[PDB]
Amino acid sequence: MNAAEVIVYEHVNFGGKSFDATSDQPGAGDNLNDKISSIKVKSGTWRFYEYINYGGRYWDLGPGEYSSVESAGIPDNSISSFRQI
Ligand SMILES: [Ca+2]
Ligand SMILES: [Ca+2]
């Protein structure tokens, strides 16, 4: 009775953590710079933002995979959070 798989990385492929879980965790939480990240998930829409839940860079997207490093804002991976719908 499980139909949800959200796997994302909070860093480079060969240098990041693999977060594989359904809707329940607080997105992401780690102190570091907003470097290259690997986001590959297919389930509705998700809101990505590197800051609080009421004062940060809002950026949502549909089911798709990507891994940029100069087109997603590289300020600082602090107080980052993302919820999947
Ligand atoms: Ca990152
Ligand atoms: Ca951030």
Image (cartoon, grey):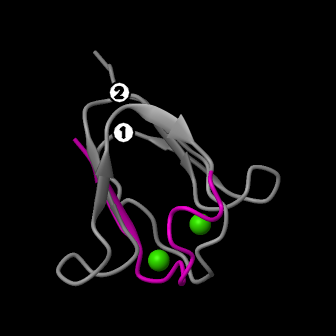
Q: Residue at x 75, y 49 (%)?
A: 13
* Residue in the foreground of this view, choosing between 77 and 60: 60
Residue that badge 2 annotates:
4
**SS majority, magenta:** loop
Q: Any mark on residue 71, and which?
A: none
Q: Any mark on residue 22, and which?
A: 1
Is 73 contained in the magenta span? yes
* Rendering coords of residue 84 (x, y %): 29, 45
Residue 48 position by quadrant: bottom left
Image quadrant containing the C terminus: top left
Horizontally, residue 14 falls left or right of residue 83, namely right
**What segment is highlighted magenta in the picture?**
68-85
Residue 59 position by quadrant: bottom left
Q: Quote the CA–CA distance across marks 2 and 1.
A: 6 Å
Q: Label 1 near label 2: C-beta < 8 Å?
A: yes
Residue 25 position by quadrant: bottom left
Q: Is residue 17 above or below residue 20?
A: below
Mark sitting earlier along the chain (2/1): 2
Q: Is residue 68 above or below residue 34?
A: above
* Rendering coords of residue 39 (x, y %): 53, 46
* Rendering coords of residue 42 (x, y %): 40, 28
Q: Amino acid at mark 2?
A: Ala
Outermost residue, front direction?
71
Does the beta carbon of the residue at mark 1 sit less than 8 Å from ligand 1? no
Q: Residue at x 55, y 62 (%)?
A: 71
Q: Amino acid at mark 1?
A: Thr
Q: Residue at x 28, y 15 (%)?
A: 1
Crowding near the residue tagged with mark 1, few <14, some 14–19, many ≥20 C-alpha atoms within 10 Å: some
The secondary structure type at the circle numbered 1 is loop
Q: Residue at x 66, y 56 (%)?
A: 17
Q: Is residue 46 above or below residue 25?
A: above
| Residue 26 in sight from this viewpoint | no
